Each structure stands twice: as structure tokens, then as C-alpha cells.
Amino acid sequence: SLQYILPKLWLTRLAGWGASKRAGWLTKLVIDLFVKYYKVDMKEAQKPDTASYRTFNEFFVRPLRDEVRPIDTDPNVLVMPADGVISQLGKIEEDKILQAKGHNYSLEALLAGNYLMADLFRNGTFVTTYLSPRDYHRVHMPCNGILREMIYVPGDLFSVNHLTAQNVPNLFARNERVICLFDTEFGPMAQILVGATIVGSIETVWAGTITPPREGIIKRWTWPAGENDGSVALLKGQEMGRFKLG
Amino acid sequence: PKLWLTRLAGWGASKRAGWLTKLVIDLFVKYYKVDMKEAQKPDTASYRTFNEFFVRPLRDEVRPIDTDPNVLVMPADGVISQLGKIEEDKILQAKGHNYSLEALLAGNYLMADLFRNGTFVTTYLSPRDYHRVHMPCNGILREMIYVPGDLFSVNHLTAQNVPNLFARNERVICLFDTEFGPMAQILVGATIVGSIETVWAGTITPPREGIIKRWTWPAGENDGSVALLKGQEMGRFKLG
Amino acid sequence: XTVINLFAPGKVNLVEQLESLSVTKIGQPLAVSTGHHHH
Amino acid sequence: XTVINLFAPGKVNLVEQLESLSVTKIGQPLAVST
């Protein structure tokens, strides 16, 4: 693995520069090569014409047709927040979360040493969903929630995939990420957006782009309980954030 | 490429290379003007590795500890970078660079709130200086936090120009109970001199596992408590 | 990339069919509440 | 490298002589209790 050798931050900035430029034919060419190599179902997209996208990023963050992702309306059901495949899921064994066969990671490591937040989730349940490059790169709410806390965590830009997940220790605990904590009818609920090499930009609908820039410090925002003025509520199935290049 | 250069220097500084070791130590002592008269072993030949020399002990007599129990004493040889009042959350780095108390403590809002409107002292250790760090006063160790970070150079130049330098560089935060309330002593690493130790835990870094780790200890009363005395060695910096 | 969810102890049961490499689509069932809600 | 101390509000006064680039030893006075 050139995972420890490669200058992952400069490659990510290069892709971000690239993916942000409005280059007509070269933009449609890279989008078209991309759609071919990765097998993107453009029939699911709101705009299936690869010509409709001013920049590569506009395409990466492309919206879907509403009807092709029906939201389970049963209020007893929490729904999947992202297109892709499950990496691992199940019980949080005290503090231990499963990364892969014979790689555990700390709940407190994942939450950037936040022992109070970790305490909410000790012996709870986790789900880790992997977004492949072909998949839709916006993230939706699993259920209704009031946003209470958001924490930006500086980190590495390791690649995320079956290979690195199986071989890089503490991958999700050391990669740049945004922790979002909501109050729900199911108690406290964390939804964590973990960046990777190239696809390193994280946004939320309430804050815009969190990263870049990369200022190298932990930043914490809080919001009040649902009752109060200035509270931010989201519904099951509603967009909360996305990943783009840069 | 600051991490690989730091590993290179650590490999270098750890090797027992007789004449090449004494040569680099001798060039070092000359260029930086090291007072070897203050050293326990003034003979540059006495040091098996460069690191043994970097972390060299001083003569017992030469750092007298002020005996007044209402005096807190300096914890490290070097020069004051900045010191004074913590303006709510804001700590002064240099002319037109402030940094957050919460940023420095890796988002630890409870610890930060103990020190809001408190006092800070930032001590710079130049390469010529003794590189062990001593207690400013008696304390019970309650909390230690390792914080992953960059390996920016620390000096007047970078302090004057790199935003949030001490809040983004790899470091070890140590929190004690004292007769003067809570007291934090923070060891911030840099390019080349990037290895941090404490007397109670050994080398914290390297290795660099990329995650925040937190250790706690009980209050002084309870069994398994760790106490240190004013002037006692608590930690050090070496290359690697 | 990746998205990680944390839920509190005894609050939800994950759909039993789901495993490593199971396909995910926005809106599909992920878990059922351990306590009964009604529309 | 660098060493940062934090003390609680109104618990110590720094010796007034100390300023940016002041020389430090290991026993020399840093602050006095209030």
C-alpha cells in the first residue's frame, strides 16, 4: 500500500480544483468515462443527460428522482441514510466497534475523545455504510430528528474500501469527519460523515461546506432542543449532507 | 515532508554510532552554544546516542526549587513565548494570532471551562536548552490526553505566521489537582523534536496511531493515585 | 466515503437479514424501534 | 518544543517581571498564589 507514501492531501486538492472547473467538453468527457468505468445508473438521476452538469462535482453530488427512493412511512422503522453497501453493523461491545475481522476501534476514538457522547452509545448499536464511487453521494436522515451538536474532526485522508478497512487500524477514527448528534423518538442518534482521499469535502444542509478549508482544529457547534426558537428539525428521508471532491 | 524527516532524525538520533554520534553531538554543541558545564556528564563522549545527549540530565545543585509553598516555579529551561490573562477563551500566540482554549484542549469543553478567564504561560525550549519538563507545584495527576496533530516547526518565525500552531501540532495535555485549583501542563511537539514522554507512562509518541487517547487517575485520597512534587521531572522531548 | 450511525442501548433492532456487503438504498428499512409508535 | 500551562481564574498572579523572550530556569519563580 502507497497509503502511507502518497501525499493524499495534495491529490485531494488537485481533484477538488479539477472537479470545480466548468470545462464543457473535458467535463462531459471525464463524467462520461466515469459513468462507463463505474457503471452509474443515470436512469435514477433527476437529469440523466451527462451534458446537464456544469462541473464534475455538480454530477458527483447529482440529485435522484424522488420516486426511485421511496421512504418507509412506518414511524417504528428507521431507514437507511445512504446508497451503497453495509461494511459492518451490530452491537457496540461496551466501547468496541467492529471495523473488519480482527480490527476493533474505540467508540471514544471515533468521537474524538468525547467521553460524554461516547457514554450515550456504550452497548448500543452501530451501522457503517460504504458509498462506492458509482453510488449517490448525498446522505439522508434515518428518522425525524432535532440537530443538537455537530463536531468537525481534523484527520488523515486514507482511502475507504474493503482493502483499507481490512488493513488500516482505526481508519474511521483517524480520517477527517463530521459528527452530527440528534434527539429522536429513539433517544440520541449519531450520524457521522467520514471523508476519504479525493472525496474529502463534507457538507450539511444547515451549514454548507464544513471542509475544505482544513484549519486543523476540532470545531463544535450546538443547537437547542426542538421546543426552543432557532432549533433545526429534519424529517425521515430528508437530505442532511453530502460528499464531493476536494 | 515533516513526518518522514522526523522519523529519519529519530532513526538517526537512536543509533549508537560512536565517532559519528560524538561528531554530530560536537557540531550541535558548537552551533547552538550548549552550556555542558550544567550537564551531569560534561564529556560529549559519555553519550551512547544523540538522543541520550538531547535528553541529558543536569547537575543536582544547578536548578534550585523555590521553597515558598505559595510560589509556583518555572517547569522548563528556555524563554517565555507569551503569558498573561486568558481573555475568555482567547490565548495570545503572537502579534495578530489568537487561539482557542477549546482548540488547544482538543474540543474538551469541560476542561476548557475550568481555565476560562484564567492564566497561561507558553515556554519555548530552544535546541541548546535542557529538554526535560518539571512540575511547577505539587499535584495529583487526574487526566492525560494524547492529541494527534501536524509537526509544524515551533519558533518565533512560525509562532508569528502559522495560525493555531499549538492547537494543531501533536501534543500531550496533563491535568493535575493542586493547592491552586486545576492546573494543565501541555507538551507540544514539533518537526524533528516530535517524541513526548511522561515519567508515569514512558514514550507517548511515537508511535503515531492517529487517534485521541484519554487516561484518567483518581483523586489523591484514593488507592492507585499518582502524586508529583514541585520541581520533580514529569516528562521530556526527544527526536523521533 | 462512509456514514456511521450510533443508536443508544436497547432502542432499535437492526433488520436481521442485513449483513456485511448487503446493498443499501435510501428509504429501505435499517432498524425497527423496540418501543411501539402509531399513525 | 514548547510547554503551555493553564491556571484557574483568580488563583495565581504571574511575577510581573516576566515578558515575551524572558529567560526561564526550572526553580525560578513563575507565579504567586492569591
Image (spheres, coloured by chain):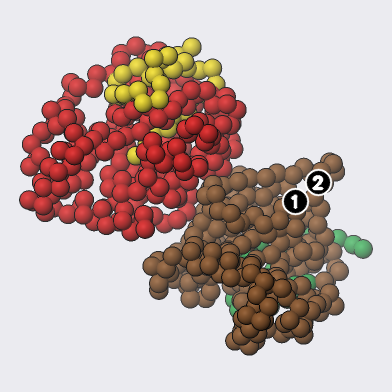
Chain colours: A brown, B red, C green, D yellow
Which x, y percent locates residue B195?
Answer: 32, 47
Residue at 62% of width from left, 80% of height from top?
Answer: A26
Would you identify the image quadrant in which residue A68 lies? Answer: bottom right
What residue did someone put label 2 on? Answer: A231
Q: Is residue A132 left or right of residue D34?
A: right
What residue did someone put label 1 on? Answer: A147
Element type at marker 1? strand
Residue at 49% of width from left, 60% of height from top?
Answer: A156
State whether residue B148 is above or below residue A9: above
Would you identify the image quadrant in which residue B174 lies? Answer: top left
CA gap between label 2 and label 1 equals: 7 Å
Q: Nearer the viewer, residue A207 or B106?
A: A207
Query: On what subunit does the disc labeled 1 rest?
Result: A
Residues tagged by mark 2 and mark 1 found on one chain of the structure: yes
Instruction: Tell me if mark 2 has few (under 14), some (14-19) or many (20+) residues whose alpha carbon lies within 10 angstroms of its own.
Output: some
The quarter in which the C terminus of chain A is drawn is bottom right
Q: Are circles 2 and 1 on residues that touch, CB within 8 Å?
A: yes
User: What's the amino acid at mark 1?
Assistant: Leu
Q: Nearer the viewer, residue A159 or A16?
A: A16
Q: Is residue B190 visible?
A: yes
Q: Is residue B220 visible?
A: no
State whether residue A152 is above or below residue A66: above
Q: Is residue D9 left or right of residue B130?
A: right
